[PDB]
Length: 122
Length: 122
Length: 122
Length: 122
Ligand SMILES: O=C(O)CCCC[C@@H]1SC[C@@H]2NC(=O)N[C@@H]21
Ligand SMILES: O=C(O)CCCC[C@@H]1SC[C@@H]2NC(=O)N[C@@H]21
Ligand SMILES: O=C(O)CCCC[C@@H]1SC[C@@H]2NC(=O)N[C@@H]21
Ligand SMILES: O=C(O)CCCC[C@@H]1SC[C@@H]2NC(=O)N[C@@H]21
Image 1 (cartoon, chains in turn brown, orange, blue, green):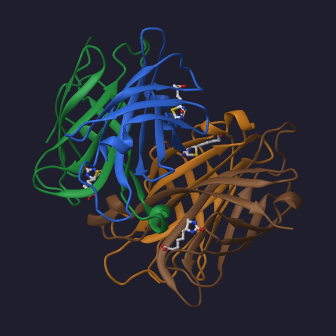
Image 2 (image 1 turned 45 degrees about the horizontal axis):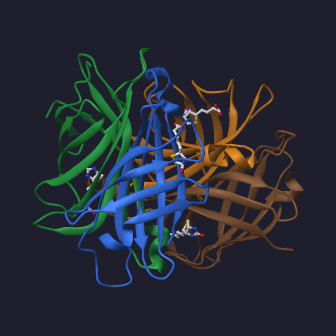
Image 3 (image 1 turned 30 degrees about the vertical axis):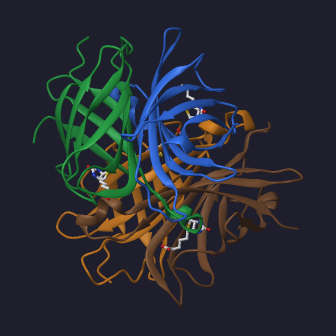
């Protein structure tokens, strides 16, 4: 739900995700990573299912962060794909792909894959 | 500069990606999939490295599509992570994650992974 | 180490992994899944780094299970890629790819991606 | 029957995969990578569906290579998951996970993901 997703969330690495869920299915916010070649906040944009299934199914969503801001540029971008599970202890469970810009020769090793779990703070 | 990301692209499945890259790193556009539980166009939003390295590296980028529009709702979302390589034959090489909203018991098989290659040739 | 990997392990879904680490870097054993189109034990074979780095780095390994045994055939195969972290509480952290045999037309949705964490039992 | 998996295959990077498929589902052979921290041949072991569906589906399979041999040790392992499609131009289409042994603090970037297509044409 927009109100359920909107808020501040943190993942197991200590990174911060601040997001606003729009009525049209849009997600905008900022992300601050606790690891990597990153410093300060980065803009994020994404989309979510604004009319999810009325059962105990999660709400599918995804967002992207290109790691360039006014202080640093890592020449990479990460996309998180997952689902929001609301409730008393709402969590957003994701898997992500982090691609670095590389020359053609090194393209085979351009993408890392991982998973992050986010917990919402009050 | 010289980032011919803006335009209409097609992937190996025949899906159509129409995007506009903003000078500050935003990607906005529509996606029409030739496969899956989809019909017509869907809104996409993403981010890209607006200041890539000056060596022969590609430009990292990523975008998301929540598969809900006025015609259908598949209760899923896809994120594409990859890089743009320009020149005579430009391409956007990506790997994607498609997550469907599931119940807790089916969460283990909620995500599909694949790769798409886009060109401006139909 | 072979002795550290050898044993019975269980993951968060309740599946059982029984493996033997060979001196030559081989892994053989059986796997019993708590979910999916599976019943009883399946043969698994894999490889691991038998001469890992002497620091607090994990030992890289991987294994495969084709989901066909004498009782059932799911026409799929899963490969787990990860690292073994030994100690008092040794764990094997992995990410996996599960591919189903499909017709060419449905190949785009043939592979699921996920992650499993295994705990060793005494 | 009619599974021409046994043989020498090459992927788009020029790597060589030599495998023997056993009547009961085992895959054994050697791998020589054209890229990465590798030299010469490495042992691989895997599994495949020895009784695939009788519809036009591919045969699911997977294999692992731990990158240690008498010449080098990269302290990593790769697992390829995919399916074999036979006919005039047979192919093995795969997605892979390459995990490097890391320390706990770098575990988040321990795994690379990519895709390789193998053909019997050099
Ligand atoms: O190093 C880079 O290329 C940019 C920073 C990457 C940080 C990654 S994104 C996925 C994972 N989850 C996080 O919170 N941070 C790391
Ligand atoms: O079936 C669904 O859940 C929605 C449509 C999914 C279409 C996918 S997204 C990745 C791949 N690339 C495409 O162009 N289409 C498929
Ligand atoms: O349903 C199938 O196609 C065969 C069974 C798949 C079980 C999967 S493998 C990855 C995940 N981890 C497990 O322990 N079981 C599921
Ligand atoms: O660099 C390493 O850690 C060992 C060599 C990795 C080679 C990889 S495995 C996936 C991809 N496919 C290949 O044929 N080679 C690269």
